Every structure is written in structure tokens, then in C-alpha cells.
Amino acid sequence: HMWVQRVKEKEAELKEAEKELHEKFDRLKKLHQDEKKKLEDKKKSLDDEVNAFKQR
Amino acid sequence: GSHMWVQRVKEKEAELKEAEKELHEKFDRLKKLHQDEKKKLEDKKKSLDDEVNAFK
């Protein structure tokens, strides 16, 4: 019933859902980048511990 | 001695490299899922547009 009205709604909702999906994925990439940078940070500190304390 | 502490630090560095690999693999599965979800929305919009155009 009222198929013309169903379609107006579903198009607008699809545009909003696509924006929402894009925002969600950006939030996920920010968290992923935080976890990546934390691992890189740890590895750089170990590298620099060796360089500071190794015998010369 | 034989710089055993340096060998230990390099093992820890290799553990972090493995952890980066696992993070990359896990994040790729989340990317694939996001790509699936984006394609799903696009095909909803396509079929709606095609249904609408079918009349005109």
C-alpha cells in the first residue's frame, strides 16, 4: 500500500545509511591506527634501547 | 658475555612484528566486511533506481 511513498522513504534512508556506514568505517580506522601506532611505538623504543645501551 | 640481553630485545622486537601482522590480518577482515556492506547498499539503490526507471 502506497508504493510511491515507500520508495521516497527508502531512497532517502539509503543515502543516510551510506553516510552512516562511511562515518562508522572512519571511526574504525582511527581506532585501528591507534593500535598500529602503539605497536610501532613499542618497537621504536626497543630499537632505541639497544642503540643507547649497547657496548661501544 | 655474548650480548644475551640484546638477543632477548630482538626477540621482543620480532614478537611486535608478529603482532603487527595479526593486527593487519584482523583489520583486513573488517575491511572486507565493510566493503560487503557498502556493496549491499549500492545494490539496494541500484535495484530501486532500476525499478523506478522501469515505469518511465
Image (spheres, coloured by chain):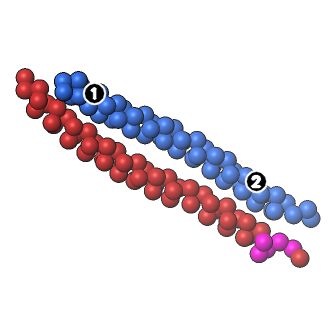
Chain colours: A red, B blue
- Asked whether, in this view, residue A43 is left or right of residue A32, the answer is right
Q: Can you say whether B19 is above or below B34 in the image?
A: below
Q: Nearer the viewer, mark 2 or mark 1?
A: 1
Residue visible at 56% across and 60% down? A37
The image shows residue B49 at horizontal and vertical percentages of: 26, 31
Q: Give the quarter of the figure containing the N terminus of chain B.
A: bottom right
- Quadrant position of residue B35: top left
Residue name at image x 26 percent, y 43 percent: A15
- Residue B10 on the magenta span: no
- Indicate the secondary structure of the residue bearing disc 1: helix
Towards the viewer: A55 or A36: A36
Measuring 72% from the left and 70% from the top, which residue is drawn there? Answer: A48
**Position above or below: B36 against B7:** above
Mark 2 vs 1, N-terminal side: 2
Report which residue position mark 2 lands on: B11
Secondary structure at numbered mark 2 = helix
User: On the image, numbered disc 1 is attached to which residue?
Assistant: B50
Disc 1 packing (10 Å; few <14; some 14–19; many ≥20) = few
- Which of the two residues, A10 or B25, is positioned nearer the viewer here? A10
Circle 2 marks a residue in which chain? B
Amino acid type of the residue tagged 1 in the rendering: Asp
User: Given the current orientation, which residue lies at the most extreme left position?
Assistant: A2
* Quadrant of the frame with the C terminus of chain B: top left
Residue A5: percent from the left, percent from the top? 10, 32
Q: CA distance from mark 2 to mark 1?
A: 58 Å
Q: Is residue A34 above or below residue B46?
A: below
- Amino acid under disc 2: Glu
| Span highlighted in magenta in the image | A51-55
Q: Position of residue B13 (x, y in %)?
A: 72, 56
Chain of the residue displaying label 1: B
